[PDB]
Amino acid sequence: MGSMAHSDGIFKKEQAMCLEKIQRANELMGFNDSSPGCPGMWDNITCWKPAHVGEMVLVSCPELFRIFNPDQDMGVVSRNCTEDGWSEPFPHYFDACGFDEYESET
Amino acid sequence: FTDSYSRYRKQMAVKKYLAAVLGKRYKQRVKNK
Image (cartoon, rainbow over all chains, first blue to last red; front, side, top):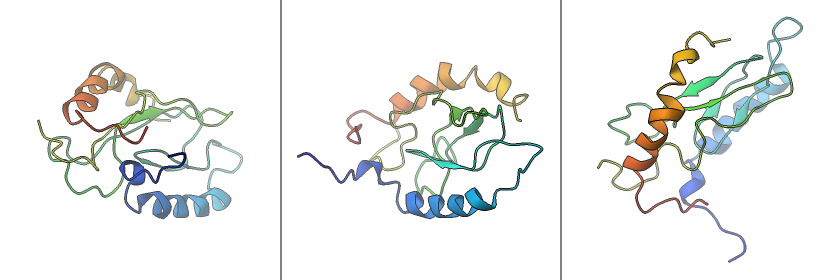
């Protein structure tokens, strides 16, 4: 009752699988002192690669008409990345793309 | 630094897609929250 497993927000293995490669890109990076930014991040529906300063990444789900098998990168959410870090979701989240849904069509 | 491509994308993202995809598929879900 207090703690839920959240079967809806499980995003398959993509949660631990993507966050694992982002952790490697975190300490290894590739920006240095020229074009800084974020070291990577993982949200509630899509994977985010290390972005630069003032970058708005819009990542949509493969085939917006035939959303069946979810590989990676879903729900087009544009999150900016300034020098302070990551900004707020816009479009907002609240379950962006339907991948764990039943009959998503109609 | 893709602000040149995301410039016009802010027209069909938070404006259109917001209610389009987050309303067509979902109907009795939103159990994650």
